[PDB]
Amino acid sequence: EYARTCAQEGMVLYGWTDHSACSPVCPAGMEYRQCVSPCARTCQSLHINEMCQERCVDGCSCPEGQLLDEGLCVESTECPCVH
Amino acid sequence: SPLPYLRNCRYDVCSCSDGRECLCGALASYAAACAGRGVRVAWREPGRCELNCPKGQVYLQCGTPCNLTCRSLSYPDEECNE
Amino acid sequence: VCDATCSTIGMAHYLTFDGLKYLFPGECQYVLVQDYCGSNPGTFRILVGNKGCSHPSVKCKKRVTILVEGGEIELFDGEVNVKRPMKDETHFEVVESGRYIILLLGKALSVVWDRHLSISVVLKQTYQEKVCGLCGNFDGIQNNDLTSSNLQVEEDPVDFGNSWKVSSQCADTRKVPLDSSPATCHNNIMKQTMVD
Amino acid sequence: DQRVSMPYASKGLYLETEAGYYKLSGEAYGFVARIDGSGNFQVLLSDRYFNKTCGLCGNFNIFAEDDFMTQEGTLTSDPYDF
Ligand SMILES: *[C@@H]1O[C@H](CO)[C@@H](O)[C@H](O)[C@H]1NC(C)=O
Ligand SMILES: [Ca+2]
Ligand SMILES: [Ca+2]
């Protein structure tokens, strides 16, 4: 909470969870990224920049690869087609 | 998309003399259109004009007109890919 | 070859560039028409966003954002806001007449808005099979207008519509049963004949 | 009274999983609620509701000392009564 309120005041503190030894709970595959982009990278998504530039929010997202697919990190190569 | 067939069925049932036959021929047209895309539909029931064809017959769904008649026996080498 | 106009007829109906009307009651923000289409360079990315209008009602807000040559304009509550300014301001001309706002966004691209719900983008033959979005590719052929973003033709307008959803985490519109009397005419035959 | 799917978008409220946390946004009304994995709540009221809100989070005035206004309109000092 001390992080989150301090983040809401306009000065987000970075990497406080490195040695806190406590981390927030998140679904398997994703790690608690301090100031993750609210703009995800789902496999079926149109690449529209400058229209998804909302404020950053703390939360947990997939690893560096592993684009989202219905709340389950999968490698960018295996994005399934939909019809 | 079954919208055109819906309009066709309403028109046929209201306008024609015998609404039973028109309804059971409009549903059949839609079913044939669907089965032209691979999707077979089982729409026939006692309240929906299940075919009562002669006594020595029986209704099927995926028939085999290769050997149904027996001129095919008279001409076996003749192709029957159907 | 004459010009061509999209049209957002009513609140959930669209009229593509090749004269195809369809029904798509969205809730999210969609790509009404864009030029960043395939291997083309592309210039503009007009977007339309629905708010509270899956069921056509008297709230039904709409907002269009035009991302043409850099800066982006947006139309909301009968007003035009130029959030970021176009780099060739010689082209921009927001002429207002009658009950409509007419935006002249260059040579071949223009937009007509009736301040409430009707939106119509007008193109000249410059584009001519270079666009896509909820308005088809504008190539004279009316059959292939439902090509979703996956470059495949969909037989159902709602699928082709959800394909153009800008944010891939908001709600897909449901496949509503097909009936003539949508919501309140459902069992009110009196009202049905009245509206007829 | 009926369980619904997710995401949900009716009546101007958008309910979706953002960054792994369930989120309920109502920007038309100027509010955004959120629930993380462990179960914490988080409400982001707007600024139009300045000095206007009245609830278990206290009125939204810059002062932090008069935030225990009960429903009767009288300030208390024991959090449980508030
Ligand atoms: C808020 O409203 C109260 C009650 O009318 C008034 O006493 C107070 O001065 C107001 N405070 C601010 C910050 O406007
Ligand atoms: Ca076309
Ligand atoms: Ca206070």
Image (tube, coloured by chain):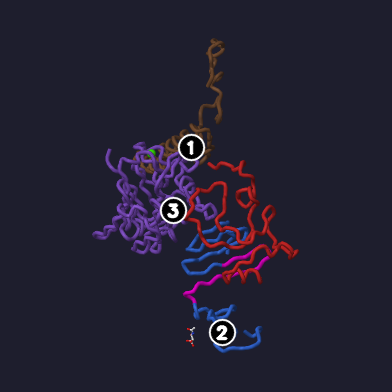
What residue is at 34 percent from the left and 37 percent from the top? C140
Q: Which chain is red?
A: A
Between residue D1 and residue C168, name the one nearer to us: C168
Between residue D34 and residue C60, name the one nearer to us: D34
Is D46 in the magenta? yes
Left or right of C189? Residue B79 is right
| Foreground disc of the pair 3, 1 | 3
Disc 1 target residue: B49
Disc 2 residue type (three-letter): Gln
In the rendered picture of this protein, how many numbered marks are placed on residues? 3
Q: Which chain is brown?
A: B
In the depicted structure, whether residue D37 falls above or below residue B46: below
Chain D painted colour: blue
Residue B19 quadrant = top left
In the depicted structure, whether residue D61 falls above or below residue C46: below
Disc 2 target residue: D71
Asked whether disc 3 touches disc 2, contact meaning CB atoms under 8 Å apart, the reply is: no
Q: Chain of mark 1?
A: B
- In percent of width and height, residue B56 lies at 55, 24
What residue is at 30 percent from the left and 53 percent from the top? C90
Quadrant, the N terminus of chain C: top left
Identify the magenta region.
D33-49
Disc 3 target residue: C25
Disc 1 residue type (three-letter): Cys
> Which structural element holds mark 2?
loop
Chain C painted colour: purple
What residue is at 56 percent from the left and 58 percent from the top? A38
Neighbours of disc 3 within 10 Å: few (<14), some (14-19), many (20+): many
In the depicted structure, whether residue A76 falls above or below residue B63: below
